[PDB]
Image 1 (tube, helix red, strand yellow):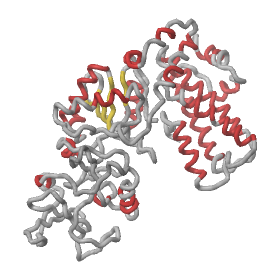
Image 2 (image 1 turned 180 degrees about the vertical axis):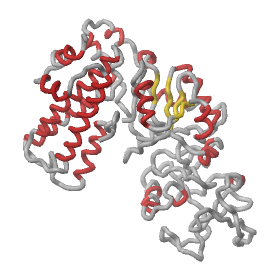
Image 3 (image 1 turned 60 degrees about the horizontal axis):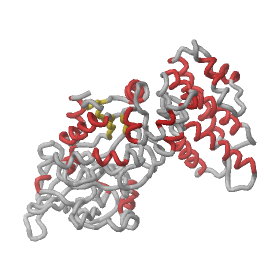
Image 4 (image 1 turned 180 degrees about the horizontal axis):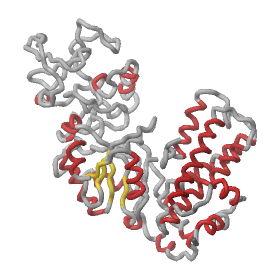
Length: 484
């Protein structure tokens, strides 16, 4: 909260103030991913970042740290055996995938980056080896299996592994640069740093009607029934909000919020930055191959504070006091996961990520009607789990928030049971579906205790025998809970 996030994060300080003006302007909480000081020496330098071609991260030490280099030994793959080559085959496969703007060049740097860690107390620069017809600056590090070598009058890190000892990757090479790919912006050199990232985005509720057109919002005010008045925030925003564009260029946002992020990334230009796109994709959990759960989350409120969190248990309160537990906006990242069981799309991710272990599953490459009806019944799973994590519920009272946030949890569990009411399905999914039914029993329970319901979940489930309707079988779920 304020001072404790500006000192410990390691970001650029003048640009977080440049994001602060739009927060007063457009009433937005702007979440962030923590990035270190070694990368933001390059962010304050004016170099652009990578897109989403390679997925390495920023090294904790180094004059070349913060980059996505050729060899991934100088990055987050530090101390791995095959991942330092599985990552080395990742950026070399970005050559033949994103070709058209991928180059091949030594890094862009200054000569004053060798004194960056001399005042940090990290690396010890020792003996000096002579080659290239020049008094050359050999230098050591904390690891003796990799040492840097930066020239005295150039910007190249012409490093090597020590030739008297063995490489841990398995290679054998002398004093050599990093051939990091470049962003060929009009031919100007700009190699690829690990990009300044996000964690989520959350404006106020007010700017929704001022961003998306209120020509249809003048028809939801002309709606008599309150339950179907909440259908006006439902279907108008399904075709507006969740119509993403997952790419490798700017960030997975819709056209009412993708237009807003470049406004957040233009206030850095006149106050320090010269490299344009410093934020090039979305969240930490918008790594589209696997999510990365964190403890440290940075955010600037609409009023101007650098809010620092400590654990997610505080952030699960900070979601349920500011993000979802307040008159605000829940635009999140798309058995003790006490508030966040993973998404329907991550259940779709967890669908495939266990059937690649064994063949026998729920529905396969077959032609039986029961297999596609189970595919038709998992269609209602993801469609109803979407309204679990949905900010279409604060329009009415906070009772109407928590009513529909478990009404789908009742409405899914019967369809979950109807998926479980099938043939003898193999336990790569059935025992995975026992993990499905137990936590959905748990999150409805904690909600019912925080509310004043005082009913067990299993008693209420046998009350709600909903056949197909929500026009009365939400109302009989209403009339059991509300009016008290």
